[PDB]
Length: 327
DNA sequence: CATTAGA
DNA sequence: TCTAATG
Ligand code: NA
Ligand code: NA
Image (cartoon, rainbow, N blue to C red; front, side):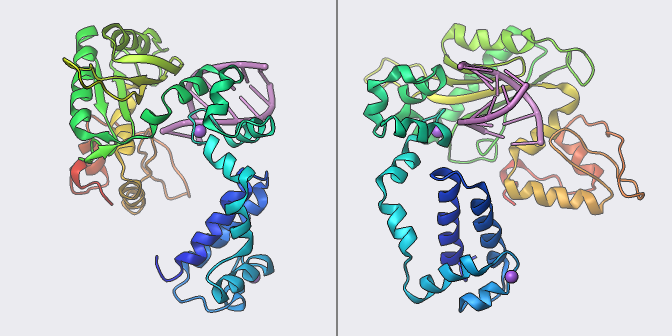
């Protein structure tokens, strides 16, 4: 957690590089396992060899360990950190809709700078274009202050459109976090569940709504179960407008809410833990359901839920407020 | 790990 | 169709 961090962090530095600049899934996958194990390791790594004993830690990595242990630096790292091309890819990648595949492709073409992108807004697709369009706004955090204003609006329409709607703004937001990245609206409705052959307009109705009013200003992607967009707070009697923000909505079968809701609310750890807990308590929990375990090895049978509570009960736990969903 | 674009 | 990009 700190006793072997540099090693791990250098490792991840390395790893990530292979994945992105180079197209070396393997090496990249190497660095990651290695970083994982060493990370586990209960002692201070003092040398390659000691490291090397490790599973996944070969001669390659060990080698880097020593050089780093010796000189608190690495060349390959130092070389890469320098490398314009590689620096370039790490950056373009920040543009929403820009992957590494694209990042290289763009570079090769010679698009390195943000402006480069602008000069050629044509070589970019709608997603990427909007990505670029709102680059600055997409990088800025979301004050809960705004979260509250945002949430409030979304809820208001949802209800206005159909009273039978169920929405939940999951995430950190939900976990009481002071700020957030983008807003996540978990959606469902009774006329939709596991079997009931859809009702795409169920999704569509709302979206239209939020656009209607002008909260949604753009669509990244819209499918029959997941809308990916950008929204905006109504720049008051201005002198102050609002940054453009990422927003996502997803329709859900009412018979799978709380689970998802459980799940999207997190935290990353709280889940796992809550997840490990169900296992002992004779269960299984995943993004959609909770199913009683059967000794034979595995087992099915999706237990009926009506609130985050049911799930809790099932594994016989303490209701944990979103607030304290921290781990 | 699944859901969307696009080509 | 596959393949990429987001979460
Ligand atoms: Na080994
Ligand atoms: Na990106």
